[PDB]
Image (tube, coloured by chain):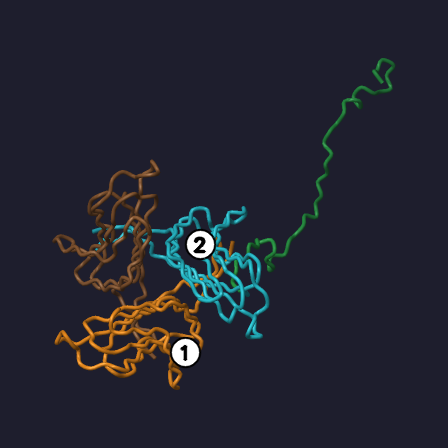
Chain colours: A cyan, B orange, C brown, D green
Amino acid sequence: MKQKVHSVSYLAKAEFEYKNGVYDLVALPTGAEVIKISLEVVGLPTAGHVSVGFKDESKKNYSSILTLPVNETSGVVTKDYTVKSDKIVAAEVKDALAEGSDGRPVKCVLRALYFLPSVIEVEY
Amino acid sequence: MKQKVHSVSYLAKAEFEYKNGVYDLVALPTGAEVIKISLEVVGLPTAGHVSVGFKDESKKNYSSILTLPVNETSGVVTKDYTVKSDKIVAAEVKDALAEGSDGRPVKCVLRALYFLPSVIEVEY
Amino acid sequence: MKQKVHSVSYLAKAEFEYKNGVYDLVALPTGAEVIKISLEVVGLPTAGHVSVGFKDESKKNYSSILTLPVNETSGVVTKDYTVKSDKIVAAEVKDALAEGSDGRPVKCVLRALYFLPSVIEVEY
Amino acid sequence: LNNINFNNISNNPNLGIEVGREIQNASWVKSPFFSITGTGADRGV
């Protein structure tokens, strides 16, 4: 029994304030082993969607991987990802107005747990 | 592309024996990045609920975040947490009698994967 | 507040080509803290199931823990595991023919995030 | 908070750009005419 495993893992946490726009949340290296993406809505939104996905450092390669309507206020991507030139995790809010029902601004927190491309050899 | 990430991660595993009471399972530091809480029931319970949640080191600030009835015997919190003075993960069993249907006592295992508040700067 | 935690974590990624057979994907040490198993299907299968489970290094102790039909193409185990002599994560495909609808062979990727049995003492 | 900077070492202070006191000019060409011209009666100019 012998294998190569990723021994280095990072967590990136980034906040944005949940109104229309595009935000570049997490930067990933080539060969990164993205194993968890979680999005959370802190507050009480009244209308809008948040779409998180992957895009290039420069060019317009955005593609949503997780969509969150107002109601559930939390989500996790159902899929695991190896970074292949799509080195930006990004989130866009197309519909959103002011906070709503609270008076206090609505937050969105994205946490990305990913393993670095480096590998080491271990036998058990 | 440059950011700060959490580079230190711990897993805490704690067992309790699934009968009425309150147990302080996992201790977390301020600023900890709790990214996974999982609860497991080893055995065949006959009646009861397990509620895991957060509470203070001292004062009575308990609030359930995951409730488990008898049937499913396993659960994971759907939400991610930054520790803000709620530095105890705790679990309470309000209804439970002896093991039931087995003769062998029923176990509950809680695993908490969390990232330490420390950050480092990385550019990719 | 003082505890012992697992401070060492590895990720093992292994590919197989999605046709009938048994594959030994990930090797785990005794006392390993398996906290995530994820299976992914890269391509468009037409018929078949993939069952991932645990088996011994030698003897025929295979038992499926996650079954994936053709349609969903991705899955994650709902349960957390401490390695007790079942030190092989294995995957079997009982039904599968050639790629189907694509002309390009169908891949399956398994990622196993697990914490090493070592513990350290920390107080917060 | 803690989004991708995209900034470079350019817009990072603590650096302190230094500029060369020496200027080098963009003149190198030399036309042949100075060799042609002369006070002799037989020079081209």
Q: Which residue lies furthest to the top in this view?
A: D42
User: Label 1 crowding class (10 Å Cα cut-off): few <14, some 14-19, many 20+?
Assistant: some
Disc 1 sits on a residue from what chain?
A: B
Q: Position of residue A123 (x, y in %)?
A: 23, 53
Between C30 and C76, the one lying in front of the other is C76
In the rendered view, does C93 fall on the left or right side of B25? left
Q: Where is residue B83 in the image (x, y as percent from the top left)?
A: 42, 73
Q: Position of residue A34 (x, y in %)?
A: 39, 55
User: Label 2 crowding class (10 Å Cα cut-off): few <14, some 14-19, many 20+?
Assistant: some
Residue sitting at 21 percent across and 49 percent down?
C92
Disc 2 sits on a residue from what chain?
A: A
Measure how far apart labels 2 and 1 are at the Cα level: 32 Å
Between C124 and C85, the one lying in front of the other is C85
- In the image, residue C97 sits, relative to residue C6, either above or below, namely above
Q: Residue A17 carries which label?
A: none
Task: Identify residue type, mark 2.
Answer: Ile
- In the image, residue A66 sits, relative to residue B48, either above or below, namely above
Q: Do labels 2 and 1 share a chain?
A: no
CB under 8 Å between discs 2 and 1: no
Instruction: Find numbered disc 1 in the image and state the secondary structure of the residue it sits on.
Output: loop
Q: Where is residue B44 in the image (x, y as percent from the top left)?
A: 19, 72
Query: Closer to the observer: label 2 or label 1?
Result: 2
Task: Give the quarter of the image for residue D15.
Answer: bottom right
Q: Name the residue under label 2.
A: A65
Residue sitting at 29 percent across and 56 percent down?
C112
- In the image, residue B53 sits, relative to residue A108, either above or below, namely below
Residue sitting at 87 percent across and 19 percent down?
D39
Q: Mark 1 points at which residue?
A: B86
Number of callouts in the render? 2
Residue sitting at 29 percent across and 76 percent down?
B50
Task: Give the quarter of the image for residue C100.
Answer: top left
Task: Identify residue type, mark 1.
Answer: Asp
